[PDB]
Each structure stands twice: as structure tokens, then as C-alpha cells.
Image (tube, rainbow, N blue to C red):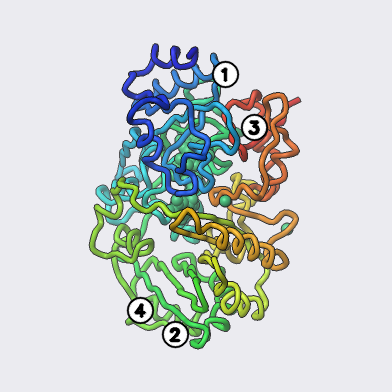
Amino acid sequence: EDFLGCLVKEIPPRLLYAKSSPAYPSVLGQTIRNSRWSSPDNVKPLYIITPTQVSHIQSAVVCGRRHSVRIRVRSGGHDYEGLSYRSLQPETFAVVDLNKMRAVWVDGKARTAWVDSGAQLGELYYAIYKASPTLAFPAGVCPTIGVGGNFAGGGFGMLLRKYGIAAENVIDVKLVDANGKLHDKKSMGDDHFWAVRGGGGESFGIVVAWQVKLLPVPPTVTIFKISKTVSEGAVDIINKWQVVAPQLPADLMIRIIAQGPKATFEAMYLGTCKTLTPLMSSKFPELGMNPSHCNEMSWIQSIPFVHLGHRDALEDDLLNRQNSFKPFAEYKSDYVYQPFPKTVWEQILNTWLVKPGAGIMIFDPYGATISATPESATPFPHRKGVLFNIQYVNYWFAPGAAAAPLSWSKDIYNYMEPYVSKNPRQAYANYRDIDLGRNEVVNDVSTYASGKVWGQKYFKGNFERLAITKGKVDPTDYFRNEQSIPPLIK
Ligand SMILES: *Cc1cc2c(c(*)c1C)Nc1c([nH]c(=O)[nH]c1=O)N2C[C@H](O)[C@H](O)[C@H](O)COP(=O)(O)OP(=O)(O)OC[C@H]1O[C@@H](n2cnc3c(N)ncnc32)[C@H](O)[C@@H]1O
Ligand code: NA
Ligand code: NA
């Protein structure tokens, strides 16, 4: 009551929703992307605020401090555990939902842009396209991902070998801190500005907007998608890929999707069929690539083409907010520094991918620019020596069908333990996986020791600096969730 009273005083009432508001269920559900987290057994926010101005965010945070009510911020709602809009255990929180703050302003000539956190990647990419056919930004593959969470947790996609992660291409921010204060890079200082760009969402304050540098791409890029079944030699070919792909020139990224005894090699090349053909013949002849495989197109066209296989529907694929794809979903991730033995690839393709509840495995090769950044230069530590990342994705479509995929996800992660990174076993912060560990709260503050268990997996040697920065900007642990950076204070 106290908290709501404060909000009503400062923010338009049409932007405030209580559980009893008729529109609350659809406001809550509008960017939930995982059917596991939409059902009524999930813990719901007491209130939802949908700011349209930065002053509304500040008022909301000031109210939350005064009345001791915590806020989970949501931009695109893609959090794998839904931590932008649900808690694991009953507790009081409000959601500050940024979907209405979605402006993107591109300065083509300066090659910079200001992008609101509530914009989806598709909208950012489209706006860049309206400004220039030869500029791009290196962020996620899926068009509906929110800018806010994608950037805060790092953010990578088919330009990662060329330009690294989204967070290392951010040149300023506009942020509201745990005391409701408005900050930019200059006011927040090196530590806070280092942490917010890749140190995970929520922990370091609400980013309202990000200023990004825009990067050159040729007017024509080339995509191929070449599949090999095991009888076509997928095992030998992927065994070679793991050594070659991380060593390829930075203009060529070849990722793999596998969902049975068959691997599809999806490439984005910053250039033409005419130069890709000889490069492949020279560096990776085992794949058997020829000019018939080439799909030449602009960078903007490559986004729906890579993610959805569509060539013909630019605006609908990039500017969509209908939220129609809502699988029940589980996800895990690993990083690989040493080549798998051929026998492991044999097991993966022939055995693991043919079990009840078996999911899809995606393999993104590193090296080049992403690996050239030192491990501590940003909070994202998965850099020098990384051959590839693995994402293990399970989708299902009926609420009664969870047992087999959940069980497969657990089993394959156990199987893979000897072959992937260890001490710690690294994982990508934006592929959030609560089973890596969760925080313990003592005297209303997340403990450092509990945070460290999962924190070293996402952030490796960067965890302690993240926590010291957290202690400086938010010593009372106001902006938190079950897996956010704990404050390390003296
Ligand atoms: C759903 C999904 C997710 C990803 C891909 C595809 C699809 C369909 N593919 C992908 C991803 N990540 C990549 O780097 N490359 C890819 O190709 N996926 C994961 C995605 O990057 C993460 O889920 C990301 O955190 C989602 O961001 P979001 O859509 O904005 O999600 P939430 O609103 O749930 O927020 C996540 C997390 O960050 C905090 N948060 C949200 N907004 C802010 C702001 N403005 N400031 C600070 N912190 C923020 C949330 O509280 C939550 O903890
Ligand atoms: Na290690
Ligand atoms: Na999970």
C-alpha cells in the first residue's frame, strides 16, 4: 500500500498494474518467452510498472528504496530462467518493464547509435539498415531478444569472430542506479562502466539506453547451410571443424546445429561466393562446399535468413512483437579449450542426440577478434584459447512432457564434463542456468560465497572485481535476483 502510494504520486496511473488490474495478465505475459514460467504456479510480481520516460524509472526506484520493495527489470523477457519477471520462491517484488522505451536513433555519419534497452535486437538492426546498407552491430541471432539483457550479459552472434561481443562495442550508457541516480560513463567511473558491459543483467542498475559504435560490413555477405549425416562423414568432418573453424579468417564464421546423427554447418562470410569458394577449398575442403551452396545477400537480410531460414519478409521477421513462439524450454552451455577425441563426436551424434528428450546442440567457434580481447578487459572471460561454445537446447510443447528433456539435459551435461573447461566449468551468463548454483541471502544480502559458486563459471577471474564494484554501487543488494552479483564490502 505504502509502496503503491509512492508510485501513484509520481508515475501516470495507466503505467501501473496490480494483480487485480484486468490488463495485468497480458502485460505480465507479453514478453514471457518460456512456457515453463508463464503458468500460475510461478511467483508473480506484486506490481508492474511500464515506464515511458526515464523519470518514471527513477521515481520507481526511489519508491522502492523508500518502501523497501525490490524491482526486477525486464527488457525483452528472454531470460532463460525468467528472472526478469518471476522469483524462484515466494517474495514481494515489482517488475519494471521497459518495452515501451524502444527508441533507436542512428547517426550513420558518426557510425554511432543510441538504443533504448526496451528495443528488440530486430528493431536495432532494422534501424541501422534504414541508415546504411554497409553498417552492422554484433549482437544476438534471435530478433526478439531485448537489447537490455542481451548487452548486460555480453551478447554474441554471427559477427562474434569479426567484432567480438555487443558489450565491448558499447561506448556509453544512460543508467539508473540503486539510489535512483541518473548516470553515464563519465559519472559512473571505470569499475562500474566495466561491470555493466557484460557483468550480467540486474546487478549493476537499470540501463535505460546504450550508445553503440556501428561497424562496417560489405554490401554483400554470403550464407551457406551445409548438412552432413553420419553416413556422409559428419564425424570426421566435425572433428576437423573443431581445429580449423577457430583458426579461420575473422570474416568467416561457421557454426553448427545438430539434432540427430547429422550436423548442419551454417556459415556467415563477410564477402562474396567468388572469394568464399577458394577459401573453403583451401582451408576446409572436407566440408565439400561449392558455389551452389552460396546464398549472397545484404547483412540485414542475413538476420532472418540465419535464424529462421526466411529470405522474403524483412519487416515482419525483424519488427515483430506478437510473441507467438513460446516453447517450454531448458538450456545449458559449455566452453571447449581442447579438441574432443573423435570417439566423443561419435557418441554425441550417434548416441546422445538419439535419446528420449534429446535436444539440439549449437556449436559457435571462437578465435579471431572475440579471443583477441584479454580475459579481464571486460567481465566476459571466454576468450583466448576458446575453440568453441556449446549450447544444449531443449524445447517441448505440452506441460506434461518435461521429464524426458530435463533428464536428458542433466545426463548429457554429466557425460560432457571430462571434455569441456573445468575448475571452473565455464558457461555463458546470458545462457542462464540456475542449476549452476543460486545465491543464499543472509540478513537480506546475497552472500559472496554463494555467488562465487556460479559466478566463477560465468565470469571466471572477473567475479571478484564484479563483486567489489557491486559493493560500491549497491552495498545493500537492492537490485538482485537468485543469480546476481553479491556485494563484496569491508
Ligand atoms: C530467448 C532467446 C535468447 C537468446 C537467443 C535467442 C532467443 C530466442 N539467442 C542468443 C542469446 N544470447 C546471445 O548472446 N546470442 C544469441 O544469439 N539468447 C539469450 C539472451 O541474450 C538472454 O536471454 C538475455 O539476457 C535476454 O535479454 P532480454 O530479452 O532483455 O531479457 P530479460 O528482460 O529477461 O532480461 C535478462 C536479465 O537482464 C536483466 N535486465 C533486463 N533489462 C535490463 C536493463 N535494461 N538493465 C539492466 N538489466 C536488465 C533482467 O533483470 C534479467 O536478469
Ligand atoms: Na580451467
Ligand atoms: Na534452466
Q: Name the residue under label 1.
A: 68
To which quarter of the image does residue 450 belong? top right
Q: In 3D space, how far apart are the residues under numbered discs 2 and 1 (Cα atoms)?
A: 62 Å
Decide if residue 212 is on the left or right side of residue 463.
Answer: left
Q: Do the residues labelled 2 and 1 touch (CB within 8 Å)?
A: no
Label 4 is placed on what type of residue?
Answer: His
Q: Is the residue under label 2 in contact with that under label 4 (CB below 8 Å)? A: no
Tell me the amino acid under the disc marked 3: Thr
Marks 4/1: CA distance? 58 Å
* Dot label at residue 293: 4
State the image coordinates of residue 150 (x, y, percent, origin top left).
47, 46
Q: N-terminal of the two: label 2 or label 1?
A: 1
Amino acid type, residue under disc 2 in the picture: Gly
Q: Mark 3 points at which residue?
A: 469
The residue located at (38%, 73%) in the rendering is 224
Which residue is denoted by mark 2 in the rendering? 288
Q: Distance between the residues labelled 2 and 3?
A: 50 Å
Residue at the spot x=63%, y=65% of the render? 412
Picture quadrant where residue 297 is located: bottom left
Helix, strand or loop at mark 2:
loop
Say above or below: 105 vs 363.
Answer: above
Relative depth, front residue between 144 and 404? 404
Q: Can residue 190 be seen in this view?
A: no
Q: What element carries label 4?
A: helix
Disc nearer the start of the sequence (2/3): 2
Which residue type carries mark 1?
A: Ser
**Of label 4 and label 1, which has the lower sequence position?**
1
Sequence order check: which comes first, mark 3 or mark 1? 1
Label 1: which secondary element: loop
